[PDB]
Image (cartoon, coloured by chain):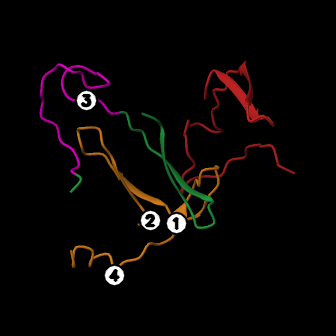
Chain colours: A orange, B green, C red
Amino acid sequence: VSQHFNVYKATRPYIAYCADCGAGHSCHSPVAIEAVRSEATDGMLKIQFSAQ
Amino acid sequence: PGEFLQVSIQDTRNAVRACRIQYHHDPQPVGREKFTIRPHYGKEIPCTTYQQT
Amino acid sequence: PGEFLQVSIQDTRNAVRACRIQYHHDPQPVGREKFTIRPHYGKEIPCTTYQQT
């Protein structure tokens, strides 16, 4: 609708430090992982990262 | 199951940008049996999930 | 870590040429802990590698 994504017009993706960028080396990543939540007893897990 | 987690995307130049972290992730189901895949004939037990709404 | 090793290429006819050998490869890192991914906070210990030069 109109204001359903009115929340995401005021926020931007950022760059944070990732200590292992796939090759064993650190970098400043646009997809840095912030937290993994595993509360669903189903077996499903929820990842929060830097991009949108 | 596995000892790490990784996410990755393609950038505009089409390179791969990834982040990798240490995460344990050994999940087991509900009930008194450690199955792997739902059968075609069984019982129902309450479980929780993350709804996609 | 795995019980074999395999390398392959793509020939002119677009076929796959692979060789597979038996190799053990159970590697562990330096120090007194068996970690999987390097941390953001840690300590620096000497280790050796193969330089690409």
Residue density around tag 3, few if under 14, some if 14–19, many if 20 or more, within 10 Å: some
**Is disc 2 surrounded by few (<14), some (14 to 19) or many (20+) residues within 10 Å?**
some
Per the image, the residue denoted by label 4 is A10
Please state which amino acid type lies under the numbered disc 3.
Pro
- Along the polypeptide, which appears first: circle 1 or circle 4? 4
Q: Report helix, strand or loop for mark 2.
A: loop
CA–CA distance in space, label 1 to label 3: 34 Å
Query: Percent position (x, y) of residue A14?
Result: 47, 72
Assign a secondary structure to mark 4.
loop
Mark 1: few/some/many CA within 10 Å (<14, 14-19, 20+): many
Q: Amino acid at mark 1?
A: Pro
- Mark 4 and mark 2 lie on one chain; the one further toward the N terminus is 4
Question: What label does residue A30 carry, if any?
Answer: 1
The chain holding disc 2 is: A
Closest to the observer: B53 or C44?
B53
Three-letter code, disc 4: Ala
Q: Residues within 10 Å of mark 4 (few under 14, many from 20)?
A: few
Q: Of helix, strand and loop, which mostly describes the magenta segment? A: loop
Mark 1 and 3 residues: CB-CB less than 8 Å, in contact?
no
Q: Secondary structure at mark 1?
A: loop
Q: Identify the residue at horizontal 60%, vertical 52% (top origin).
A: C43
Left or right of C35: which side holds C44? right
Residue B29 image label: 3
Residue drawn at 17 percent across, 19 percent down:
B41
